[PDB]
Image: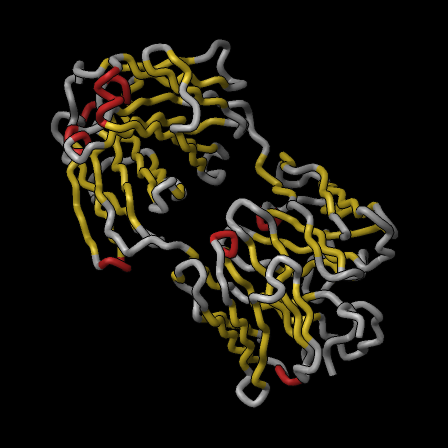
Length: 228
Length: 9
Length: 213
């Protein structure tokens, strides 16, 4: 039952600071070295920092050296990562990772074993904004045989995430809510498309529900067919 | 101290 | 300064297939190599440590070998739980990971269904025009979507998003969003996306004219 739970993730503007925490349970936190690993969107996994069991030794990756500080509080079973002078490239999912621990610890060089589920840190000068939901209207251009496509464009929201729900009763061959894309404005955007029977386009009602909790926005939009 | 050496007790 | 390279980048396989993925190091790391498994939305899990030793609870179908610069991870019989991404990690000089290797579900080539959506009038009233091109249920994932405005190939004004592989039909779905200003949208009349895929004998073009809808 070795369990590592990250906390403190969220939005932080560039040049500012944020501290992450990691709650350790199921093992002796005081007896284990700990790691921080991050995965920048698109880029692969990269090691951030390591701290010794007693806090006496700390090493960092060159990309975060001089801006990031790793700490621990063995009396509270908590690991810390103080991030300062944050840049957009520091936007990533940060994982709390335990160093390799064995009872017959006769090893020379040590890696990592148990990871936490991770927390997301979004570094941007953008402000919290609810999305604008626009209809992707069905038409002959979005119909192929007995299957038609329609959807909703969820545009210009920050931060992540949003939840797009389609109404029950919308006969659906498949719902594809695409991963978000970061636009040049620093705002996110996604589409949620659904395949429906072409027979029901002139009768069935199709409504998408977009809920953006950070802005407390819950918007429903009906997608109506066009003559095209 | 080698950063890859044993970081545990 | 130890780089880890993995081949292949994407591996297509089926249930029961013997799967082998290779990891190379820029220098000799002896056996100080580890293999991790990460399924989407879930945290990485350590499968193999010291190049070849299996971790506790890891199924015996997983196997690892190598010493020095070249390493391999082998799954003798591929199970449904084994479809994920695998990373190798060296722990000799700091900790660096490979770019990852995704094990996807092999299936027959499936051509994409191409749909195009014109901008809504509500979005045009906000001063921006987004045209969306949908590629639905296709395989393999490699697909080329090109935007043409008045038969002029567009660069820099589109962004694409692809879904993960759906367990139902082992297919992918892709969207391409062309974003223009209302001033530029009304300058031109013809809008089209061209899709090039292995399941298509010729590039498929769906188009629409501003004002027809």
